[PDB]
Image (cartoon, rainbow, N blue to C red; front, side, top):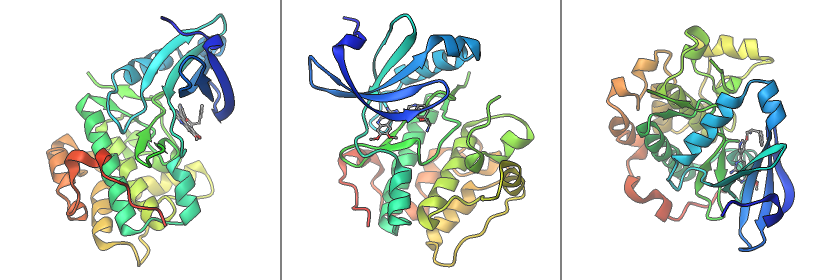
Length: 276
Ligand SMILES: COc1cc2ncc3c(N)nc(-c4cncc(OC[C@H](N)Cc5ccccc5)c4)cc3c2cc1OC
């Protein structure tokens, strides 16, 4: 039953990294399109990433939700590992933010709700993403979200993500929790409304300085209820963020006035609002 590289017609490179390359492929027997993540075994071993790649596959194997990438199959030849992932036709959320400038209230609410629902599922399995950002949140043909890149995920019973979305506790205690993803969520909501992430500076050190000082400003147009939500997620104390266990979880987060009109139970059945 195991698949081979010969079973596929590979196409364009979708993304390139230091440890992997994601290529679009059409399976010959089925005509199905997959995003195949290809990882060179020598380079993984040389840079000591075996625990990272192993955990990545293990985390993706446990994912069974429409708002997350699916691992359909794995195989290997002499040089490379292949992970067969779901293909998200419409690409990164980041593309759409830069294209339309900034989302309106209807679109901000719907896509934020999808991210919250995704995170609720994810954190309910005791998994932290640790690198949540618009480029890691993809969009399928139906324009629903698909969160990918679990190469730096943490399974709860050491890394530092992307600078602009890094939480203060990671800069202070080197520790990561579920609340770290929720901080990232707050940056993402801000970015959807404002067009740019909240903490911006000339270099990483200067960005990290702004994070620990909570040095950011809202534009005047910023949706009042969206602002209130962001202010309750961008909190230096990870214990005081909406959604976290110490704040009694996802109930209160989902009950926030910004989500008033949201039907939480069937988001992926709903038709997404058009991005204008
Ligand atoms: C139409 O366009 C696209 C469609 C797509 N469909 C499915 C995907 C999938 N299941 N996983 C990834 C994915 C999986 N590990 C990591 C990752 O990124 C991490 C970094 N940012 C940069 C990077 C990108 C690729 C490989 C290594 C590093 C992305 C990407 C895609 C994907 C990407 C597309 O365009 C960017």
